[PDB]
Each structure stands twice: as structure tokens, then as C-alpha cells.
Image (cartoon, rainbow over all chains, first blue to last red; front, side, top):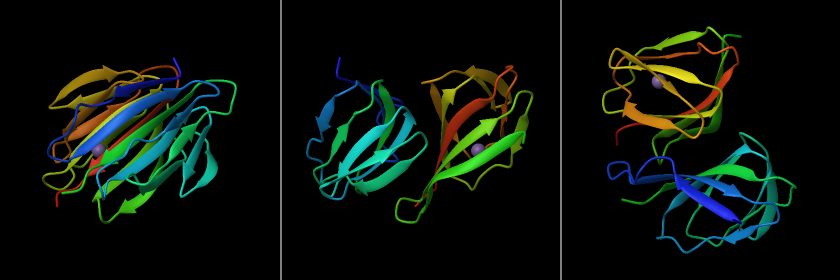
Length: 95
Length: 95
Ligand SMILES: [Mn+2]
């Protein structure tokens, strides 16, 4: 399977916060779905190498490297390495 | 040394949130002072095996597993495995 998503914790009503663990197979590309205005997303690489397209530009992130950005803007996740990439996606929804 | 701490992101003023990576050497024990009242913490194991003491009780956590708990309680981290343990710690402060 190209992309396997698993919540690390259930939806957190108090913190308005989701925390997902995602494994992206070699060669897989995933485009973000739309989010509510004001959502903030953090991506942190756990293992492997991840390519993130943010503000129309690609960058490579290595383990324990991360990026914080506007989750409501189009972005993409891509694995151009030869092994799965495991990363976390944290989402803070606005109050 | 026994414990190596690294911020994954700098302090987030708007989200009142810290995010750290920690590596505990075999046999290491870290006893934290309780954080401010209302603080919520999450811990996720990246690799290895982590023991955590919450509510005066020890439990062992493995990769992909995590726990959410009240940060203003006393708690502790310990590595009783023969390998280092690498984990992430999230801290959310009250707004
Ligand atoms: Mn702590």
C-alpha cells in the first residue's frame, strides 16, 4: 500500500489536536486534502527521507527534521528514496 | 551522556507547545519536576524500549506506542534495556 496512516493518539478535544503516524512507500506521492482556514501542520521525519512540497517548492527532510506550516494551503508528500519513509503529521485546529 | 535532549521545533508562542527528541542511554534514569498546572504531555517511542513512571507505577513503552498524561504530576523515564532508547516528548501549556 502506497500510504498507511495511523493515529498515534485519538482526536484530542481539549487540545484540538491530531497526531498521525504515516508510512509512505517508495515512489509514492500524496497531495494534501483541504483543511479549515488557520490549521497548522507539523511534519517530523522519524525514519527514511521525505520530500515535502510547501509554498510550491520541494525540500528534503531527514530523521528528526521537521517543518511547521499552514495546513490549509496545498502541499504534498513524496518518497523518492528506495525504502519506506515514516513521518508524523501533527495538526492543530483553530479555536 | 546518559540523556541527550534536542528541540524538534523552537518554542511555539501561538500554539503554547514544545516538541523534543530525547535519547536515554542504557541504565539511565531521569526524574522530572512536575511542569506547570494544566500542562499535557505526550511521549512516543521512536526506537528501543522506554520505561515510564506515571502515578507511582512503571510501564514499558515500545515503538509506535505512546501515552498522553498530566505533566503537572511527578513522573520519570528510565532505560532498563541494553540499547539506547529514542523518544519524542510533546508539551502543551494551558492557554
Ligand atoms: Mn516531562
